[PDB]
Image (cartoon, rainbow over all chains, first blue to last red; front, side, top):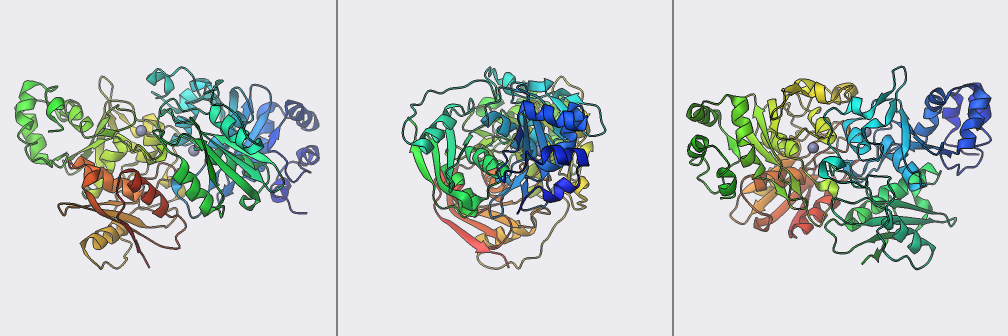
Length: 294
Length: 292
Ligand SMILES: [Zn+2]
Ligand SMILES: [Zn+2]
């Protein structure tokens, strides 16, 4: 009868608890809401969209894995499709600060890896840090993305990132979440296809090093992550983190991993192999193999 | 002579005043206060205009091996010393191992014992990663950021509604004096690595680490771990040592021996990233010294 949501649920208004309870019954609730589910919660609570997003933040934060700090952070990315995607921060004991995932990166890559074409807004509890402001300026929403914070007026990303640097200053015209297909041939079994398709839609205009990770779980589920570079370089999200983000957001723990594949080019400018191996080993996963692109 | 090209870009008077200061092949990529004063006398520039004019020399120190876009920065210490920085990118590694020019210059001043910075001068607006990095320093949001053809501004101007160590109630900020007290012993390179760990900044994980590199001619360069309140802009200890190595006019083939000092059972572990990055740079003599 375990549930990562129970304690957080007690902190929610009674009407929202009742409304979302049928949606959270599945232990592997996908930590996203279809547009019709957003409408159902609005009807069952009377909240407008901004207030409902704020009210849901404790459930997103309850998905987080702050194994080092114990400080749960949540975020909700609102797609133009009308779907909303939860994110939570992730920290990895035995790895490094560079492997950590902020809640904003978690929610944004959640939307992107589920095929959302762009975001209209993001809702958080605390002002995104400079690393996240730089991450968001990679997106096709650019400086116009609406940032929603409790008890304050909504503002565009421009408000938080004066004199911004981003892909346009590098004359990049295909932005993160724009449609991309690098055309590597897809073949093999379900997990191999997934890893190659993840690499095919990755965002890497600075190093031209495509990469993707796919994980196959004990119950047969596959989650994949696509590499997402950033104009400022360091806020880049590696492909492993995207896959681990989805795995955790979907209610799994790292021992659920039964197979793991990294698809990349063995002689690309940048190589994800070593960090992928190291971070998986920190999580107790020793089973990782490479599918070679090109 | 990695400065020869950049030197041709300077005004004649500045060229003639500084070209002697760059005489030694391993010019330490910093200027003493008396050297800044000499350059000011020989050009009549105020310190802001001099720093702007010196940015091509700092940028000449950079190693943008991926992008080929050199970025320079000049960190003005409260001592009056100026410290050059340049960006570093590492082929065969990842985007996470990158060092921004601002991080380079601040790390330079810090590892040379500068107590705090009064300002930083750059040619391009610092990115959000660098704005967050700079909010770790004991100069806080008041640090002055100087950009060409722009009004100078506090870091507060570039990072509204900032998050930093002060929000986590950290009272020992980056560049404040720290000494974690681990016992120093062994050969010179081992002691350098332990000393590097003793002055590192790690209030979030309490995972101390330092790296020391021994070059073929016997020179040792070390780097201390520097965490960041936002976590990801953290500078690993290896990056600090490679920064110093390159800024002082060396290339990675000169590395003969490398040591990481850290706690075996620490919450965060630098060993695997350190080995993998050094291996991408052709160094395979890497040992680990364990802190109590
Ligand atoms: Zn952040
Ligand atoms: Zn930067």
